[PDB]
Image: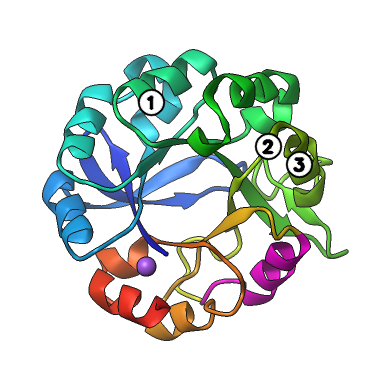
Amino acid sequence: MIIPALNLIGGTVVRVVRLHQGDYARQRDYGNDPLPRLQDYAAQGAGVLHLVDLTGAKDPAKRQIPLIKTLVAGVNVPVQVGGGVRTEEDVAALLKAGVARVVIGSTAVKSPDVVKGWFERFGAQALVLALDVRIDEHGTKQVAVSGWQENSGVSLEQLVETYLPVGLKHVLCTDISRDGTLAGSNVSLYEEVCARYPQIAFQSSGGIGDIDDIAALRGTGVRGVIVGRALLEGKFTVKEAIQCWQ
Ligand code: NA
């Protein structure tokens, strides 16, 4: 399924780039109209919508709950939301606002015992494990908690195996070398991890540049294709992407 994605800083739809140390920097503003944008996506048939709340990522006290509530109320498919989700109270607040699935990032690497508790409390269908991956010179799929600078000492597979016994189901795997590049996604990466873990519903993220890039993912076993920039820049429509995917 095609999963259109929006990044939000204080009500504004933005493009961000990842920096050397993993931090996100703003590049350009697309506009102050997330609701009509999401509704355009939803109306065209998007099966899931992905939001990153960068304001809340910087300070969880400033989680954009009122905005998120209005966006969920405007659509009729699951909305998944990430952006520095670090405590169970943060997860609960998002779910209470009507978010379908909460995307969990670096906390799942740093504090696995804590996050295992979240799976027990919230259930596997409400949680998406985000894995930002950099494939190093040795072929290891490094999970980046700090971008390109330091090696986390944790692999994609190590983390997937960590959470399978508590029922892990959804994994968002971003290739950080392809994020925002319009290169095409890392097809062989997704072919490999999807076959390696048939019980996991993987979402691909990063690199989609044109309709052919969506076609290239069709046989991989990927269950969701996240598309940010190419939809925002009008390379193709959500309708066209769905017609291609199916
Ligand atoms: Na679809």
- Between residues 184 and 216, which one lies in front from this camera angle? 216
Q: Secondary structure at mark 2?
A: loop
In which image quadrant can residue 107 be found? top right
Q: Which residue in the protein does label 2 denote?
A: 167
Query: What residue type is disc 3 on?
Result: Leu
Q: Which residue in the protein does label 1 denote?
A: 95
Q: Looking at the image, is mark 2 or mark 3 earlier in the sequence?
A: 3
Asked if 141 appears above or below 209 in the picture, the reply is above
In this picture, residue 194 sits left or right of residue 244: right
Q: CA distance from mark 2 to mark 1?
A: 19 Å
Asked if 102 appears above or below 212 in the picture, the reply is above
What secondary structure do most residues of the magenta stretch adopt?
helix
Query: What residue type is disc 2 on?
Result: Gly
The residue furthest bottom is 212
Q: Secondary structure at mark 3?
A: helix
Q: Looking at the image, is mark 3 or mark 1 earlier in the sequence?
A: 1
Q: CA distance from mark 2 to mark 3?
A: 13 Å
Residue 113 x/y as whole percent: 74, 20
Q: Which residue in the protein does label 3 denote?
A: 159
For image coordinates 83% across by 58% down, the residue present is 140
For image coordinates 22% across by 59% down, the residue present is 41
